[PDB]
View 1: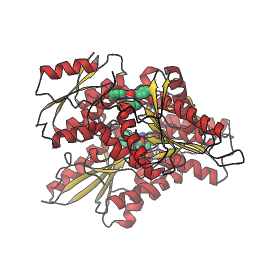
View 2: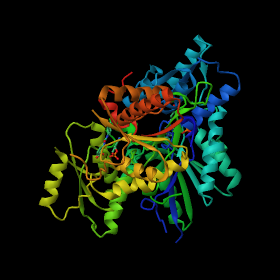
View 3: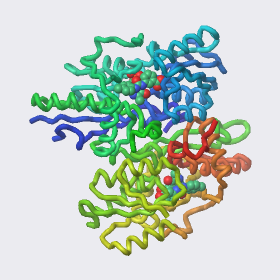
Amino acid sequence: RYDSLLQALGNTPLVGLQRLSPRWDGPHVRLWAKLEDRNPTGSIKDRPAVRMIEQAEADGLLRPGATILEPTSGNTGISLAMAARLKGYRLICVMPENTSVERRQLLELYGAQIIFSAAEGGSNTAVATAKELAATNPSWVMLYQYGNPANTDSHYCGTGPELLADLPEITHFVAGLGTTGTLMGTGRFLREHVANVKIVAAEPRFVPELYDPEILTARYSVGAVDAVRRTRELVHTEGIFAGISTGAVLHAALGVGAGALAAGERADIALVVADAGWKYLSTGAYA
Amino acid sequence: RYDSLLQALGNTPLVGLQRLSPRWDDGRDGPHVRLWAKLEDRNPTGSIKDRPAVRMIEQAEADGLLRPGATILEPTSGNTGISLAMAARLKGYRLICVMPENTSVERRQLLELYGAQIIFSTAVATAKELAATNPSWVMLYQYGNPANTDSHYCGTGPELLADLPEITHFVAGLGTTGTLMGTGRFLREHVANVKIVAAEPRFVPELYDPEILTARYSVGAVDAVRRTRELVHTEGIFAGISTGAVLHAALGVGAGALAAGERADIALVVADAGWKYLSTGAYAG
Ligand SMILES: Cc1ccc(NC(=O)Nc2cccc(C(=O)O)c2)cc1
Ligand SMILES: Cc1ccc(NC(=O)Nc2cccc(C(=O)O)c2)cc1
Ligand SMILES: *Cc1c(COP(=O)(O)O)cnc(C)c1O
Ligand SMILES: *Cc1c(COP(=O)(O)O)cnc(C)c1O
């Protein structure tokens, strides 16, 4: 039991995918899904968002009633909006205008102000916009998820240890590459404990300051169509209603697994389910 | 770890509502009056219905009622349908849901994604008639199947007692009545003087047992929507609309304890999250 929604975070389930795995029972090639939608606002960003705020509190950077400013494509904004309601802060998000309606509904419900940046240039445009706002009003506190080490540390101290506890036999960890915190933190932790572990990025077909290229074994770029087809496959075969990035991660993980199978090598491949499908229904991807 | 999503069910968190509670800390003014929220959206398909749905299907399988490719038929307003749709897909059954026409589009989308057939409709009568027409169809029948109540007697109740052994009250919505009959019978059988409190919207399922409830509150939609919004604003929990009604009743009970100067530790169910209700407008800025 917990005294705050903020504490009911992490320790997410790992679920073996018996049907989707290239070979569940030569040696096995298993996929294991870590369900990060089992978190306060339904995404993995609850981990870095809460740690970034708490670290800024510890460092003296946030006084009561302060205004937080953050560029986001939705999930981090939502997690910060939740935490800001519990902690008494205001939030201004800069978010690209071509994002799902569910994201803006959630943000408005939590009381965040949203500046909708131009679609052209996507995240780079949102980040440049947020930096421009930060410079016009220095009292606003930008935690800066793309450069804040508390993002990586949330995974070094949370995601990674939980994976190793649940799956000591892990051979590969597969996740999306956005802020890079998930892969940097989880991957640094796993490399310290697991001889020979492979860390694999999925990215959509600037460089965050958190990024350390030497943590990755490989980077796969995934198209939206393949991400949609795999997201659909995951819900049809395993019942997990995931967001689109999960489909891209699964595409990569299934590539890794097909390689292991063809080589006669045992693999236990952990993959992140970073959020659920709820915020993506309006896209038509699940029709 | 688990090797099926169906196992990653239950064992849901209980979260203290320090801001919404009438009095979180014992003080000069009198003893604490605490609200504790059980987050049943942390379940395979995002609602408490995963508990009875999985148990009903598994009980029907153990009893020898289902064969590969069997058709299951269920009257539902959406949550049980969704739960059954997911489990039927994994187990190789066909699902037909009889639903009222005025339900949120999100429900329809999730049912169709899992591959359920939807018949619109009264829904219970329509299902019963169809089941009679097609004797090979299996109608689990959430309004009368004891595996619904048992899922709460064996799951929700003991989990809640383990996390909150100081419990004074349990509050939940009254629909199929499984949650309150199961959890309530468990609690009343274990905890002297515990209060079992229903929230109902302003036929009687066969599962209903009139001796279990100690109090029953009718809550209007306006109050349910206001409380749902209050919960997200004050505690950050993005709940469904039934949770607002449950909160309304829980706060009533809490105000009573506060006025009487009595300690209370009131557990309440958050049966689903707000996701499926965004299309209603209930969560507008
Ligand atoms: C293949 C693929 C597809 C989608 C993603 N998603 C992201 O990287 N999301 C992301 C990145 C940076 C910030 C945020 C945010 O919620 O603010 C989200 C990652 C990888
Ligand atoms: C005050 C209040 C408001 C809403 C509820 N919700 C319900 O009872 N939901 C319900 C009832 C019966 C069947 C189903 C179903 O998912 O099929 C849902 C319960 C109480
Ligand atoms: C943030 C995010 C990612 C990428 O994770 P990072 O730790 O930012 O690299 C992938 N998928 C979803 C849904 C996300 O919100
Ligand atoms: C089913 C349900 C209820 C009522 O629970 P019962 O066990 O059917 O009485 C309340 N809220 C939600 C969201 C539900 O799906």
